[PDB]
Amino acid sequence: NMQLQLTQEWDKTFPLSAKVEHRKVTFANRYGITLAADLYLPKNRGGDRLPAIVIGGPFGAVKEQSSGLYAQTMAERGFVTLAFDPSYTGESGGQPRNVASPDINTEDFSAAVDFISLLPEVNRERIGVIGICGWGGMALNAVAVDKRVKAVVTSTMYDMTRVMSKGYNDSVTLEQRTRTLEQLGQQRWKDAESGTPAYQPPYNELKGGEAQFLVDYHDYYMTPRGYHPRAVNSGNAWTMTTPLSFMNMPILTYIKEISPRPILLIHGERAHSRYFSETAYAAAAEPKELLIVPGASHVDLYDRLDRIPFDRIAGFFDEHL
Image 1 (tube, rainbow, N blue to C red):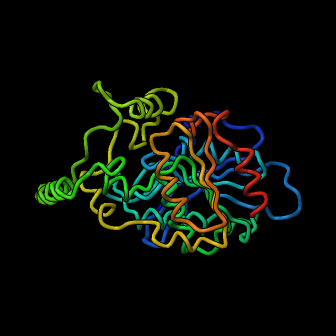
Image 2 (tube, rainbow, N blue to C red; image 1 turned 45 degrees about the horizontal axis):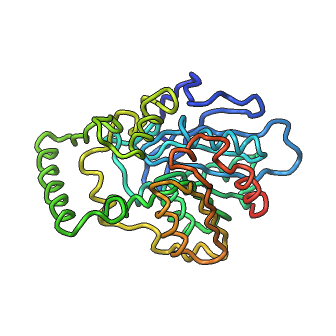
Image 3 (tube, rainbow, N blue to C red; image 1 turned 180 degrees about the horizontal axis):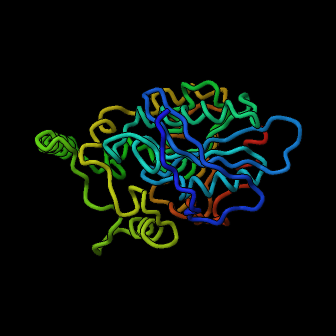
């Protein structure tokens, strides 16, 4: 219920579609934070209320990036859609800026469902969600307990609690994890002494010697391709102590309780992160499907129309919503 200043400039990383009606909206979550979002609806609508889809992700990205592209595209496919900025980020409220939590972020998804549900153009009983990158994990986490969500799709997902706790491909040992936690403790004291939290070094800046998937992230987040000034991943960062919650509170515990509702996990064949979906798929219960996109990288499923299976995503929700 906080009043937020939302820009009217079309600053999306993709052009506005003439086949959709767009406007910005706001809504609060259960923890008292007001979020900002872009709502897209099909034009020349018939008499029946429409199915709806809430889209979030990547983790550290804003609605003007990938989630927005997905939302507009699916709106062209006949769905009412919404791309939102997670708590403390983008145009959403919350302070300190750029802090995250698996709990609060999981809540953000259901706060978005709360809003899209009350729209006069939507049928609250026909709601689905799409979780991209880091929010793929949050989407599955949200659907497990939010029984209103009828189906869920994840795209090139990450389980952010797993990556922050074990690093990529479980590269963090207990000793290294303990060392990191000890350091975080020292950081809490420094932040407490100044009263304000410090931020991690700028995100996605190449120094040389970085693995290809990191170069890919830079090419998306730090070039005209997908750069947006408000995104954490676009040259900014989370607070140094953000990892404390993620490293201590895993998500997906109740992933099997999404069933009987369907899950479609989508992932590029060559993605460094493909294993996250393989883990989630194994942990999940039927109905479930792991769809591998031949030869696709991680960032390919961010904005590549010839790599993102929108036909399949639309077909999936058409049946289940």
